[PDB]
Image (tube, coloured by chain):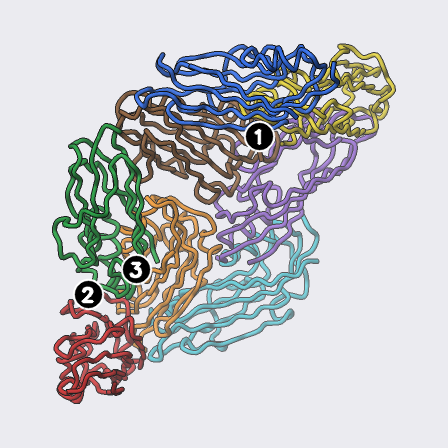
Chain colours: A brown, B orange, C green, D red, E cyan, F purple, G blue, H yellow
Amino acid sequence: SETFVFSKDNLAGSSSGAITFGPSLSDCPAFSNGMLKAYHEYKISMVILEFVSEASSQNSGSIAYELDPHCKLNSLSSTINKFGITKPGKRAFTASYINGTEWHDVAEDQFRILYKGNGSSSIAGSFRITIKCQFHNPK
Amino acid sequence: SETFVFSKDNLAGSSSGAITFGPSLSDCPAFSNGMLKAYHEYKISMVILEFVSEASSQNSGSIAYELDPHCKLNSLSSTINKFGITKPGKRAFTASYINGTEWHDVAEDQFRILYKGNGSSSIAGSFRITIKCQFHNPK
Amino acid sequence: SETFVFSKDNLAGSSSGAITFGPSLSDCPAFSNGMLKAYHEYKISMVILEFVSEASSQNSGSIAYELDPHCKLNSLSSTINKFGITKPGKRAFTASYINGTEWHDVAEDQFRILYKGNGSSSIAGSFRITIKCQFHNPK
Amino acid sequence: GSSETFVFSKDNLAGSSSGAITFGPSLSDCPAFSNGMLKAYHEYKISMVILEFVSEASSQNSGSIAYELDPHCKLNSLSSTINKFGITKPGKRAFTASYINGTEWHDVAEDQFRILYKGNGSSSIAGSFRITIKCQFHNPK
Amino acid sequence: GSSETFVFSKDNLAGSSSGAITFGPSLSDCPAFSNGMLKAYHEYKISMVILEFVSEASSQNSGSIAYELDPHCKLNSLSSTINKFGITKPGKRAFTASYINGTEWHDVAEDQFRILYKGNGSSSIAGSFRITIKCQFHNPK
Amino acid sequence: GSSETFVFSKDNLAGSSSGAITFGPSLSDCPAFSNGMLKAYHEYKISMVILEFVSEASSQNSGSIAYELDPHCKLNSLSSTINKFGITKPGKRAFTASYINGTEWHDVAEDQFRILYKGNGSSSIAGSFRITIKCQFHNPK
Amino acid sequence: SETFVFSKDNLAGSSSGAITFGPSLSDCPAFSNGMLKAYHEYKISMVILEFVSEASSQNSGSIAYELDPHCKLNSLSSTINKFGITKPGKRAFTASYINGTEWHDVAEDQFRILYKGNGSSSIAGSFRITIKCQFHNPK
Amino acid sequence: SETFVFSKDNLAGSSSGAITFGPSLSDCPAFSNGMLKAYHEYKISMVILEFVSEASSQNSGSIAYELDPHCKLNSLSSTINKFGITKPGKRAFTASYINGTEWHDVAEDQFRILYKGNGSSSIAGSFRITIKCQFHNPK
């Protein structure tokens, strides 16, 4: 079970986007263009998403994060789970929450995390994402 | 988790149809318009299909049914399983039969039950369907 | 015992209003227009009200919350329980505090939470409300 | 208090006639209860109900009687059709305390609950409801 | 060789519809046999057949289903009406090896025998044939 | 369900011919499986595979057959060359449930997995794949 | 096993540089010009790096710190580990993480910590570094 | 930790080369372009070198190999160890043999395996190399 730590940096307070975990994970070239390119199956057993708050305390807003376990959404719709952009945050998703108990082909993404902020345009912080993954059937 | 009991009523002896367990299950508003829109993942860990006989004992026929796990059939083909229109029936399908080992997106039908009767056009009975399901990742 | 997570968003620092838990809970259509519409009785066993602070640290004020277990007040009168709008908060009400030990008809609200802020008009945060409920006597 | 067990019956249930039985001060089908004990006690609770369908119907009658239990008397006609009895086959159904608002004493001027029913058969006789309510009473008058 | 026991069913037997079931390469009603084992073995013989009539008919249906056993597939429609099943009563009938040409192996390109049937009832549903064939196979492909 | 064990073989493997064997509805090399049980069951999973190379090659033939296991049928030709069998020496290789997508039932209209292979020898005969798949089936048709 | 506490002060929010642990550690003259000058071997068994936050809450930015255990980098490249300059932080590196299990000559640095901030030019805080070291073979 | 299996194929009986385990190991993209760029430190705690014989039994020679621990040799000198081209071989090197007791920078080759064959120019076989390695300090 390998471990991959990467970071989505300079998330503005109004940043909206998706982080797709699989071959589309350009944010970690050692994963999308690394391990996946030379394997058949992989499952991302655990995800640790931490919001490191670089925002000034004069920035009002929050980043709402939705964990879609099937890559069926291109934009966040659930505004329930969120971190205040002036406060550090941490969320741990286990295997059952992330569609991560059956091996997937290295061509299709396992899931995605969609983030959407409603704050001001200034830099609001960064996402440190630690995925504990497993690999199988070497090429 | 929850246990939803709903009904498909006024089934004539020759009525045919499909019960798609998921977003297409219009029969139970407590599931399709309710819990399916309050969660991301779900699985129907058990199904109990009971046939309550409203039919006259002086009418013939039966209602055959086929459990389509992957929603690949839209009309009945097989007739091995059947409920007599004058004898109430009961059939319990566990998780592995109804594809419910893993989790599904609420925009997807988990499985379906195709039913077709060969009786007359008289009211043959009702289906009481009891789905024991679990939910995940609140929306 | 089902669980429902919803959120009252964009609570301005001077926001004053009521969240009524029952058929009048428009903030969770999966509850008011979902489970309740297809059941006879329900009791909300537990409530977890968390104030997520999206307010800038230059916003002075607090949101006072009063838990009325009988829907007898249309506006907050007790200014004792409150969260500072610049600080995250969490309050857990059990069954006895919320009139939640005897089943109620799905037409009458079990209780309500009245919130009233004295801060500035800017966005002060959001309420994340997790109600652990139970349902009975299926329709 | 006083523990009573009243067995009464709503008879001549037409296969298509629909109705409702309100348990409490308006239970005219059991005059020994509505105008009986409730005239001599301040509080009652119907701790248990046993509703049974004894069928007088022939083998050729096709239909059913759907019975809904309204624990607050806020419905006046049938709404759901999940629970049902075959009009040609006797059936039984026991409701405990919680299902029928029977965990808390009610003053005799209020209705505890009701049982609505609707038959989807023909107009011939279908059967009869044998209803056994086990109740308790308090505070004698 | 390989001993198999295939249980299949011809369902929705109308009380008046007549037909024939050819056992062997053309047994479409049991796809696990016609297109199954016969694609992987040179020789088979159906050493035993158990034909059962499971009735879905009401007590008011008057008729029968006459079943003839043609051990050489040289008849295409029913000819005799001695053997028969009541369309309202389940029945059973076991054919041994000799009665069904089942004492000698047949290459998979030929039909072992067939069972013709004809109902003299009405057009309503009469029942279903539950057919259990106990067969043996040789010379794997 | 039903537990079956199908042993078939892809023969006349040229030392240089490359191909792929798709296990499931398209397994033409084992007609008793693709067109057999899969015509009579809704769900199957191939819980185990045993691929064996039985060599017909002489001592003078230099080469190997590289076999890749694609658990999702998303590759059409060989890509990797790590696993391999000597074309002159018999070999064995057992894949368990997880390695071959065999932990979850698949509807009969979808392919469970496939085994691609490519020989880097000459054009002479190299051997034959003896493949034993132990499978289970559900929901009879 | 001696202990050395020192401090890199007045780290501006945009400060970028390296702290090399060994004879090049000018920030602790009692270590580079002290113990090392009179010994042959030393290993720095443990490092405790704490960011004390002197920054005003109106300063947006973070200091990213990379622990290079071989002195092969002159500038930070990994922007994953970081402290928000408005929040105190603490990180403890043990022996295996800092190339600190085999004795080194007192002329070559054991490792280095490269810090790089992306905040404003104002004073963002200080680094308090506590190295638990060991010394061997007295001169 | 992980166990990477890669291959050096199409080795003619007289082919010579060097397998540099580290950033120069172009054979395995899952290691050189992958994990080596996802971590700072690493060590190859075990190596299993297997020689799968593709060669004809009517060809002579052998492939000798020398385990260079400190990458000081670029071409083979010693020939004590050897794999016959007609008999598959296996050799397991533990940590102390392959210099893997300590940790290394990913910009450095930990060790290498020099191989040279004295056979003809016919395809003699393939090398299946299985490195059991560990990683440290995520980049």
> Which residue is at 77% across, 13% downward?
H16
> Is the N terminus of chain C in the top left, top right, bottom left or bottom right quadrant?
bottom left
> Which residue is at 71% across, 28% downward?
F15
Where C108 sits versus F83, above or below?
Answer: below
> Which residue is at 63% across, 17% downward?
G110
One can see residue B11 in this view: no
Dot 2: chain letter: D
Q: Which residue is mark 2?
A: D79
Q: Amino acid at mark 1?
A: Tyr
Where C77 sits versus E45, above or below?
Answer: above
Residue H32: image x %, image y %?
Answer: 61, 20
Structural distance between the alpha carbons of marks 2 and 3: 30 Å
Horizontal arrangement in the rendering, residue C89 relative to residue F122 (left or right): left
Marks 1 and 3 belong to one chain: no
Q: Amino acid at mark 2?
A: Ser
- Nearest the eye: E123 or E32: E32
Q: Residues within 10 Å of mark 3 (few under 14, many from 20)?
A: some
- Nearest the eye: D8 or H135: H135
Q: Secondary structure at mark 3?
A: loop
Marks 2 and 3 belong to one chain: no
Q: Which residue is mark 1?
A: A39
Horizontal arrangement in the rendering, residue D141 relative to residue B42 (left or right): left
Q: Which residue is mark 3?
A: C95
Structural distance between the alpha carbons of marks 1 and 2: 58 Å
Residue B41: image x %, image y %?
Answer: 38, 46
One can see residue G20 in this view: yes
